[PDB]
Amino acid sequence: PRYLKGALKDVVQLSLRRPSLRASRQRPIISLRERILEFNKRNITAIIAVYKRKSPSGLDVERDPIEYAKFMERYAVGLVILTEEKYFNGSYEDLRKIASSVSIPILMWDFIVKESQIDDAYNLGADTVSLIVKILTERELESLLEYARSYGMEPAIVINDEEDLDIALRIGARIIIISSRDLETLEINKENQRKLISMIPSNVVKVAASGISERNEIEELRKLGVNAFEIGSSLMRNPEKIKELIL
Ligand code: NA
Ligand code: NA
């Protein structure tokens, strides 16, 4: 991984030791990227709803993962399921239960630093995984990206600054998540998020993440070329808010 410090260094060290699992995938790969593009063509707002029980940026919410995913299946373009355990209270069992229950695309969000974590995502039923530029070297990014594609997965590349975006382009990213939240400081900077979006080629699928809570924000980001919107804590607290955000 990169040279890190503090809690980011901690979660990366823990992820390096994450025990792998054994299971049989019993699901096709259902591409998040393609379904975004399909929603864009049908002029349907594409919201990726996040399931996360805990985070550094919110209070805990303990709610049924299957109900949440079944409710979201009718509205969301895909689901993001947290599997990081210490800081997000996620689990691979959340992802397994949800993947077994619904047929929309699923992104496993975790600090992916080794190949066995991509095996775990594939074997559990995730369609894609988050590759976070803040923690991975160029060499690690290129290698894990190729390994995920060997399973037929197209990872989402997570960025929050210009240097991250340059690396995401260098590695041939096809879907980028532009998060307005800095993973180390938890600051939300939407001016920087718009500047990053303006520098991404038109043929890369763009997902805006963090701090989105209003239909007016979505409309304005769509007009700037954003293709989909990752929305977490607002929907964890009030899942049915998705109906209004898509209207
Ligand atoms: Na290990
Ligand atoms: Na787990």
Image (tube, helix red, strand yellow):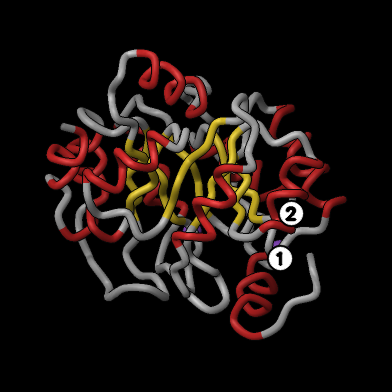
Numbered mark located on residue 96 in the image:
none
Q: Position of residue 203 (x, y in %)?
A: 62, 24
Q: Is residue 138 above or below residue 32?
A: below
Viewer-proximal residue among 133 and 126: 133
- Give the residue drawn at x 39%, y 14%: 41
The N terminus lies in which quarter of the figure?
Answer: bottom right
Crowdedness near tag 2: few (<14), some (14–19) or many (≥20) residues, C-alpha within 10 Å: some
Residue receiving disc 1? 16
- In the image, taking residue 155 as reference, residue 135 lies left or right, namely right
- Indicate if the residue with disc 1 has its beta carbon within 8 Å of ligand 1: yes
Viewer-proximal residue among 83 and 100: 83
- In the image, taking residue 17 as reference, residue 106 lies left or right, namely left
Amino acid type of the residue tagged 2 in the rendering: Lys
Tag 1 secondary structure: helix
- In the image, taking residue 12 as reference, residue 194 lies left or right, namely left
Tag 2 secondary structure: loop
- Give the residue drawn at x 47%, y 74%: 187
Residue receiving disc 2? 114
Tell me if label 1 and label 2 are in contact, CB under 8 Å. yes
Q: Position of residue 44 (x, y in %)?
A: 28, 23
For this orientation, the residue located farthest to the bottom is 6
- Give the residue drawn at x 76%, y 34%: 172
The C terminus lies in which quarter of the figure?
Answer: top left
